[PDB]
Each structure stands twice: as structure tokens, then as C-alpha cells.
Length: 214
Length: 209
Length: 212
Ligand SMILES: CC1=C\[C@@H](O)CC(=O)Cc2nc(co2)C(=O)N2CCC=C2C(=O)O[C@H](C(C)C)[C@H](C)/C=C/C(=O)NC\C=C\1
Ligand SMILES: [Cl-]
Ligand SMILES: [Cl-]
Ligand SMILES: [Cl-]
Ligand SMILES: [Cl-]
Ligand SMILES: [Cl-]
Ligand SMILES: [Cl-]
Ligand SMILES: [Cl-]
Ligand SMILES: [Cl-]
Ligand SMILES: [Cl-]
Ligand code: NA
Image (cartoon, rainbow over all chains, first blue to last red; front, side, top):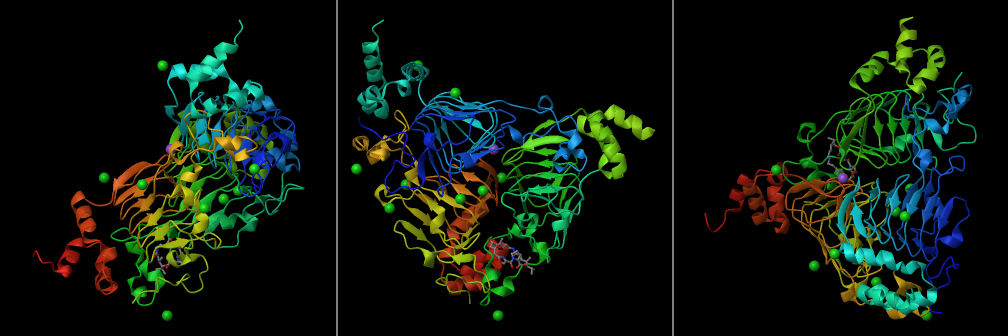
């Protein structure tokens, strides 16, 4: 039964900044898994960090489980991109006649969902651009601007984004990905926590094979 | 048709987005019509202009129909320290040190910051002293503009890197020749469908006409 | 001649620029005389030091005569997560998970942030854990200082890019040897014109050393 309640918005005692993200969600098209947290700068909500996010565009921000999201991380959804065929100036917003030129979505450089995997560590003041996919077990350095996709279990950073290194060998990465501990039962996760935490992936692999029954 | 460019808040119900020119209060800031600052929480465009001192006399110049995203910052020449020896500004602290005040030629001043027409500037861009940004350029959010940007190019990063030109040299040459931003508003309103869709062939046509 | 380095606000009418040393209250921070922080809104220098926990024991050391820009942040090692397996900080949430409290040896510590003398640090710079910045350096605004910075060099960008040395390697060696910032103020006052205009040759003479 060990562990915090993922429905608890403020699961750390005395801490008014660190929030479990899922039970704070109020808007639709934001799907965040359990235990993922946002460590706010000054109590702001995770949703306030989601920008240019309009229902009319229908783009989604999707985040998995057990993610660590640092203060000031911002998620720039698709409302940020201007029409780029002619002038970038948005005449229609000003109306008084120009409302005629309200653009159709097909004319916008739309990008699709922001998708973030599980067990992802996102540093302070990272900016995430529209359409970006970030793999399981990634680490994004502070102040990065995530301008392209991020491989699972990789470390990246900078503006624009440079790949830095792989966290483990490809064999070990493959095994973390076949393990998927974040999708296991909490009872199973607790049992395996010492090894999930110390990186004893060989042990985790044996416990997984043991349970196979296949 | 069109909003009044002297309207500080041209969109109804929107207290963040401001036409810049009717907000200008300070000297040496010259901004063209219809250019806007989409503020974060209503702060004024002027207060995004930093280290701007009259005794240096550098200017910030911005053309028409520019989109300036929230948190865009302009760093003027007052930011630069003397770089011959120590960068420490002894004179500021006086008490005898005021006599080490640098002359203007001691300082590495870099001139005016000039942004052209129809430039889209991303959220939280920082602009360095002396930078020239061409018409129709696009500056990606979070960029630190450390060097000049060509007309109709897309740039980004810290430091700034070239990403791509928006069109072929020929079409650009043609937009630059057209200079639609300097037409009368009656003519602009007439030609908006093609300014927006980039039908430059049609634009040359109607303008010859 | 010169201001009182213990005067927190050494410029008349200015409530933003602070001599840093007399504002320090925290352990594990040491900042040299005359170094200043030009705050955005009156915030203190210590408010710009982040993830600094005594139990980790990392130190922030800054030399003398440094110019520190508005918004400059110092990230110490309390931000580092364990990287052996999952980065998720289970122990924080307790309720059984506090038994997974890491040891300091489990954490990827970067050591102290050490900043030399006569350093110019631009606005909105971010300094990462364990970085060393040599004397006379210049860090461009908005830089993220991800690695060590050679003395009298210019750097910038995210991640940090080397730009150029300020002087020839010979002249840098001469500044480094002189260490004007450690000289008695009477001597520094006698030599200010040349410290400021960069005339190292003349500075060398004015000292009149034992090996002429
Ligand atoms: C950026 C910097 C220091 C900062 O890190 C801290 C500040 O910003 C605080 C500040 N600075 C000031 C008033 O508060 C201030 O008043 N400045 C700084 C901007 C011009 C003058 C000034 O003296 O003008 C004189 C003329 C009268 C000849 C010349 C231009 C001075 C130039 C100069 O020495 N640049 C060194 C840079 C100072
Ligand atoms: Cl902040
Ligand atoms: Cl994903
Ligand atoms: Cl391998
Ligand atoms: Cl903000
Ligand atoms: Cl006086
Ligand atoms: Cl502490
Ligand atoms: Cl407890
Ligand atoms: Cl160390
Ligand atoms: Cl060099
Ligand atoms: Na970069």
C-alpha cells in the first residue's frame, strides 16, 4: 500500500509548489498520467503553463506517468503559428471588416499533439514546441527549447535542441522499454522499486521473466 | 475597413494586445502603424526596451504590420561595458571614481536596432544592440537575436542561427519591390486576399494596373 | 577613494544595484568585495541562488569586482536527480517511499560553482552546477553556462559556445599574474586608469617588482 495518493493535488506535506498534475486538470485535450508532477515556481497550475491551446484547433497535450516536470516549463500548442503563405499579420483578429479574412485551419502550419512518454524528467524553464514527441525515460536539460522529437532514454538540451547522449546502452534501453514498469500494478511497482530506483535492470528483467507465464 | 491604428486596445475584450505607436511615450522609439505588442499581462511595449539612454542616443525603429510576441525584449547600447581592460563600471559608484567616466568612443556602441515591415517576432525573443531585421522575416520564440536577419528569412536559437528563407530569391525580390505596407489603406483593403495568400503574381498585376 | 563595499546600495537614487557581500546571510556562499548584483525589481542575490541545500555541502564562491546582471541564476546541486534507474524522486512523497531516500553518493553531484574576479555576467544568464569561471571573463546575456569558462574569454549561447579570447595569451598571463583585484585599494586607486584602459605594460612598471 506504500505510496502517495495520485488524486492528492499537494502530496508533499508543507509543500505548496509541487503538484500532482492529473487531479488539477480542468481543461479537455490535456491527458496526464498518475504520479506525474509539476513543481511550480509559485503555486501556479500546470494548465497555466499551457499556451496557445484552443479547442477549435483540437490539438492535444499528452503526458504519461511518473514524469517530473520542472518549474516554468511551458507547452506551446498550435495557436502560435501564423499563416506563412503571405503576410504573417493576423488581420482578422482586429475585425472592423477584416474578420472576413478569418483563416481556415488547412492554411495554417498545424503540427498535431504534444506527446510525452513515461518517467520523463523535464528541467526548469524548458519550452516545448508544438507537435513534439518525447520518449520514455528521457531527460530534458533546463532551459531547453524542445524543437524536435526526443528519443526514449536520451538526454537533450539547448536552443535549438541538440542531442547530448544516450542514458544507457541500447540493450539496456530495450529492456527498460520491454519492462514498462510504469504500466505495472502498484503492488508490482512497489515490489520492484528498489531496482527501478537503483537501475538493477538485470534483476528487473529476471523478475519480469519470472512472471511471464507464457 | 480596419481598426483605428491610434487605438491602444484594438480588439474588443482584449486588454493584453496593444497597438504600439499610440503607446509610445519615450524619445528615440519610432514604431510604424498596425504593429502590435501582445503583452503577457498588460505591460507596455516601452518597458520591454532596456538600457536605453538618451546620452547614448541610439534608436529603436520598427516598421508597420509587425507582430511582436509577449516578453520580447530589446537590449540597447547602454548594456555594453568598456572592454579595453576591466569591464567593471567604477565611475558609477563615484566617491572619487566618477572621473573614470568613459567617453562614448571608449564604449563598443553598435548603432540603432532597426526592424522592418511585416516582421513576426516570437514569444520571449531577446534582441541585441545594433541588430537589423529585414521585412517579412520570422523570428522564432525564445531566439536571441545576436546578428542581422535577412528580409523574408526564418531564424532562431541562442545564439541565432539561420533556418531557411521563406521563398525563392525572385519572389522575395518581388515582395520587396511591391512594398505593400506602404500603400494606401484603401488599396491594401482591396488587396488583402492576395497579401494574405501570397499571390504575388496577382499583386504585381493589379499594381501595374 | 571608492565606495564602501559594505554599503548595500552604493549608488544614490538606485534601489536595484546591490553590493552583494553585505547582503549575504546564507552559509556556503562567499562573494568578494565590490561585486554587485543589478536586480530587476529589488530582489536579493540569494533569491537567485537555487537548489542550494546545506546537507549537500556545495559552495558558491564569487571573486571581487564582478558585474552580475539582472536575472542571473545559479543552479546548485539540489536539482540533480538520481540517474541510475528512474529519475522519479519517490522518496519525496513518503508514505513508505521514504525508505528510498538516496545517499549523497547516489546523487550526481557537480561540486561548487566558482567565479573569479573582474567577471562580467550578462542579464538572464543561467549558471549550471559545478561550473568554474575564470578571472576577467565575459558571459553573454541569456547564456546557459554549461561548462567551465577560461579566464579572459568571451562566451555565450545555450549551450555555451566559446566566442573569443579577449587578449593574446601573453597578455592574459600578465593579467592573471598581476591579480589587480587582490591589491590594496591605495594601489588599485593609483592604477585605475591602466586597469580600466587595459595598459598592462604600464601597469607592470608601476608595480616595480623585485625582479626588474
Ligand atoms: C550596464 C552597466 C552596469 C550595470 O550592470 C548596472 C546598471 O545598469 C546600473 C546603472 N547604470 C547606470 C545607472 O544605473 C548609468 O548611469 N549608465 C549605464 C549606462 C550608461 C550610463 C551612464 O553613466 O552614462 C554615461 C554618459 C553620461 C557618458 C556613459 C554612457 C556611461 C556608460 C557606461 O559606463 N556603461 C557601463 C555599463 C554600465
Ligand atoms: Cl522566475
Ligand atoms: Cl510518447
Ligand atoms: Cl548494448
Ligand atoms: Cl512570465
Ligand atoms: Cl557628488
Ligand atoms: Cl538548507
Ligand atoms: Cl511521514
Ligand atoms: Cl568542487
Ligand atoms: Cl580568439
Ligand atoms: Na544554441
